Every structure is written in structure tokens, then in C-alpha cells.
Length: 9
Length: 198
Image 1: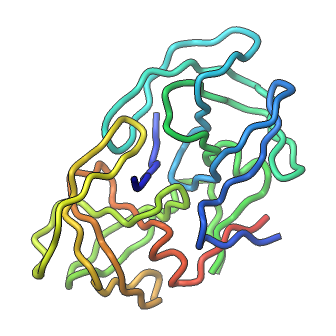
Image 2: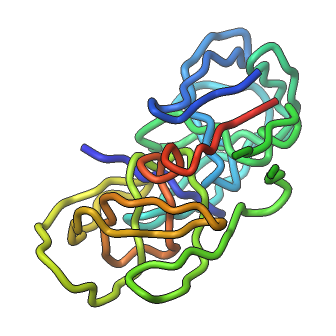
């Protein structure tokens, strides 16, 4: 499936 | 050296003496690796993505070799779906986005024009797809699930939507749903000719 790996603490 | 975005920008890293594959991710503030052992003290932290928040272990001042470049910084360890190299280490190895040049000291946010509205969006090499905050675009759509750090969200998939980004015309699939930030993914980054360079 699609991965949309935005990330922030 | 230049890395195009037609495929996921995966690289081999060396960390704690071990080799691992990780994704070069301009959409992540931090570097997050799947469950592993690292030496030294750590502190519990929480991080967030699409899908929500997860608990991680924060290890500081960890040496990481990436594309033959040494970084020393913060590495988080936790239930990420994919090993991610975020801006904290991409900046150390001198990586930038190019199409003009965008450094990664800050989140790479840019104005896009879409379905006749203007919005701020994150240029995200760690995103396969483009995901925008809820908006009532006209046209046919179909439902889809997309995954990120904290799990999955349901989105509406619209095809062949014109988007202008940094003055470059694009046209393609836009996913619309409850994302915490508007994301420009590789499907559109490739169309405007963006690459990763160091």
C-alpha cells in the first residue's frame, strides 16, 4: 500500500 | 551526485556497526529506525505522522554513515513502517532538493495552487503519493487507505488534477483526507523535475 511518511516530534 | 524520485530514495546506511536500508525523507524532521538495539542512554519520546502518534526511544549523538558521508546525531527507534533518514541527518550530509535549490534546515514548505485554491505544502521524498487536507474538489473519486507513521487514514483519490508547484505545472493523482499537513509526494515531485542532491 502507499506510504506517506511525513514525521515530526 | 543526484538521486531522482521515480523510485523510493532508498540507501544503505551503516549504524552501530550494522548495515541497513533507509529512506531519504525530506518530510521527516527526525531519523526513525525500526526496532533495533543501540548502545548508551535513551529517553522515551513521542512522534507523529499520518495516522497518529507512536512511542519511540531517543538516542543522542549516534554516528550514522549515509552515502559515504558521516553524520552524528539523534536517532529514534520505534514502530516505524520504514527506516527513515530525516532532515536532522540529511542536513549534516549536505543534501538539498533541486529542480533552484531548497536546503533542508527547515521543513521544505512551498505554495501550491490546486483546484483553484492556494495552499502551503511539504515537499516529501518519503511520500509515494500527494495528500492534501480536506477540500471539496469536483469530479469522480474513489476511496483509498494510505499508511504512514502512526497507521492508516482513509482518503479520496482524484485523478488528473492540475497542480502548479513553484511555477511548474503538474497533473496527476491527488489524495484528499484528514492529513495533519499537505504533502507533495513523488508522483508530482518527478513531474516538476525535483531531485535530491549532495
